[PDB]
């Protein structure tokens, strides 16, 4: 039972295409419980400035009422079965998933359909959601990391729909009318842009039957540029500095993603406080970089260490470090896929992203392909001598100026 | 003319080096100025906002 041998034991995810275009995917397993869900290829990047907060508002009011049963009735039905409904919205995906028992599958799928097709947008509920989101703005204001990453996206993509926040501006959510939400639903929540994904104790034909019964009535019928800018909010009274630096990364459909993951896994928090590396991926672009918290007096040293690690990977990457990174990536993948909710989310996102559920054997073969020479070449392709996007939430004063940061992206020795 | 040559035997060489350095400066000054503008454009074009709570 070697690792490569063990990967074959993973059951495949059967995929079927309905008449209206909805893609139904399942990963059956000997699990007492399952997590069904609907994933939609609609996010903030598909919204104009007129309706920037439309998707987040729809997520807020999705469980607050549908035509068949009022919001209280929907919530009571969820709670009585013991299930947990959840939803999330990214700049490119939107998911509603019901986590329940294997024998509760027939109801849950129906629930999803009731949420997806016929959503009751009560005006009073809409105003209540307005108030809730207005409070949630101040709630999110506390989170420094989220503000930093929003700054990073805004400065990196600027004049692109990929740069606006998922929540949207306060004015936009304030003036977002019901008709705008209905138009957003009509133009976006439609098959074949939907994947009904389930895993665990679910039989694929059962899921297909439920989808045809409930999710069968769904209607059948700008250049993204990376600008290496920076944003610098100071607020010197904050305890620790937050910084996120990134460069444009490849989209979802690119072989270089695995090498970049290995490079990130290869990337000393002693100088820092909590330093992390991220490889956010989108359809055609992506943010590959790092994010760390700093003392007021140690931003420069941490930035120097991070950029030195980047340069070392780009120029001279030994085989031992690359092997360690590959092992770390394999362990991270397999450990992340543990759990019913993770595999369901992976199925949905993969279908919305690759058009297919890439098996673990392919992932491991691709990782085995990765070599120190490949790591160096791809890192030089994407990291070496590239204009970065920097976002700093203060206290930032020791953060090097953009010319210094840019000059730190190449080595005079090399 | 001979007395001028005796006073300045380097006259021709001085003129030649002057022409060469004039051409050199005509090449360099716009280039170095462009380099300075390129390096300083980040500050020259940066926009700042004040957002009190």
Image: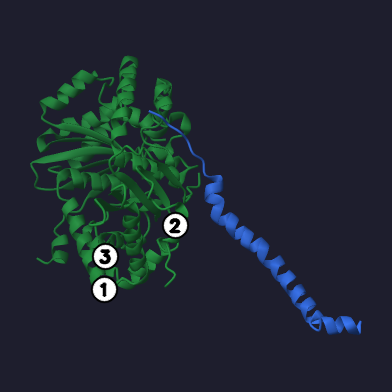
Chain colours: A green, B blue
Identify the residue shown where x is 36% and y is 36%.
A166
Among the 4 quarters of the image, the one containing residue A213: top left
Q: Position of residue A104 (x, y in %)?
A: 12, 33
Q: How much space separates mark 1 and mark 3, taking CA atoms?
A: 14 Å
Q: Is residue A50 visible?
A: yes
Task: State which tag comes first along the sequence, 2 or 1.
Answer: 1
* 2 vs 1, front mark: 2
- SS at badge 3: helix
Answer above or below: position of A374 versus A254: below
Answer above or below: position of A371 versus A262: below
* 1 vs 3, front mark: 1
Q: Nearer the viewer, residue A293 or A364?
A: A293
Q: Which residue matches tag 1?
A: A319
In the picture provided, is A386 more to the left or to the right than A294?
right
Q: Are marks 2 and 3 on the same chain?
A: yes
Neighbor class of circle 3 (other Cα within 10 Å; few <14, some 14-19, many 20+) is many
| Image quadrant in which the C terminus of chain A is located | bottom left
Q: Which residue matches tag 3?
A: A367
Q: How much space separates mark 2 and mark 1, taking CA atoms?
A: 31 Å
Residue contact between numbered discs 2 and 3, judged by CB atoms under 8 Å = no
Among the 4 quarters of the image, the one containing residue A94: top left
Q: Chain of mark 1?
A: A
Q: Chain of mark 3?
A: A
Task: State which tag comes first along the sequence, 1 or 3.
Answer: 1
Q: Position of residue A120 (x, y in %)?
A: 31, 20
- SS at badge 1: helix
Q: Which residue matches tag 2?
A: A404
Among the 4 quarters of the image, the one containing residue B53: top left
Q: Chain of mark 2?
A: A
């Amino acid at each position: 039972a070697t690792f490569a041998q063990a990967l074959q034991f993973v059951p495949e995810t059967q995929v079927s295409l309905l008449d209206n275009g909805l893609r139904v995917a399942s990963e059956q397993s000997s699990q007492p419980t399952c997590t069904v869900g609907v994933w939609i290829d609609v996010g903030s990047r598909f919204e104009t400035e007129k309706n920037n907060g439309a998707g987040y508002f729809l997520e807020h009011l999705a469980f607050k009422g549908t035509k068949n049963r009022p919001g209280s009735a929907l919530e009571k039905e969820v709670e009585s079965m013991g299930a947990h409904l959840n939803a999330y919205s990214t700049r490119e995906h939107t998911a509603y998933y019901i986590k329940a028992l294997s024998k509760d599958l027939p109801k849950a799928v129906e629930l999803l359909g009731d949420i997806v097709q016929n959503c009751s947008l009560e005006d009073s509920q809409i105003e209540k959601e307005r108030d809730v989101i207005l409070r949630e703005m101040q709630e999110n204001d506390a989170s420094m990391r989220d503000v930093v990453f929003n700054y990073l996206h805004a400065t990196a993509f600027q004049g692109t729909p990929l740069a606006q926040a998922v929540e949207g501006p306060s004015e936009n959510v304030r003036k977002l009318s019901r008709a705008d939400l209905t138009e957003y639903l009509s133009t976006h929540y439609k098959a074949p842009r939907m994947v009904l994904a389930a895993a665990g104790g679910v039989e694929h034909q059962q899921l297909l039957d439920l989808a045809q019964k409930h999710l069968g009535g769904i209607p059948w019928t700008t250049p993204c540029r990376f600008t290496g800018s920076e944003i610098r909010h100071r607020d010197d009274a904050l305890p620790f500095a937050h910084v996120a630096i990134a460069v444009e990364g490849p989209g979802w459909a690119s072989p270089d993603n695995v090498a970049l993951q290995v490079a990130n896994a290869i990337i000393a928090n002693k100088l820092c406080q909590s330093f992390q590396t991220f490889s956010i991926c989108y359809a055609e672009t992506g943010l590959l970089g790092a994010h760390f918290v700093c003392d007021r007096m140690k931003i420069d040293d941490m930035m120097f260490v991070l950029q030195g690690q980047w340069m070392r990977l780009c120029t001279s990457a030994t085989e031992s470090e690359v092997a360690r990174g590959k092992n770390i990536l394999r362990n991270a993948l397999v450990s992340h896929l543990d759990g019913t909710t993770p595999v369901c989310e992976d199925i949905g996102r993969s279908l919305l992203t690759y058009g297919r559920r890439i098996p673990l054997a392919e992932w491991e073969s691709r990782i085995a392909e990765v070599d120190a020479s490949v790591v160096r070449e791809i890192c030089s392709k994407y990291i070496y001598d590239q204009c970065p996007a920097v976002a700093g939430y203060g206290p930032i004063e020791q953060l090097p100026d953009y010319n210094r940061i840019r000059s730190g992206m190449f080595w005079l020795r090399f | 003319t001979f007395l001028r040559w005796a006073s300045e035997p380097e006259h021709d060489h001085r003129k030649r080096m002057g022409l060469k350095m004039l051409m050199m400066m005509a090449l360099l000054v716009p280039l170095v100025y462009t380099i300075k503008r390129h390096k300083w454009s980040v500050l020259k074009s940066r926009k700042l906002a004040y957002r009190p709570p």
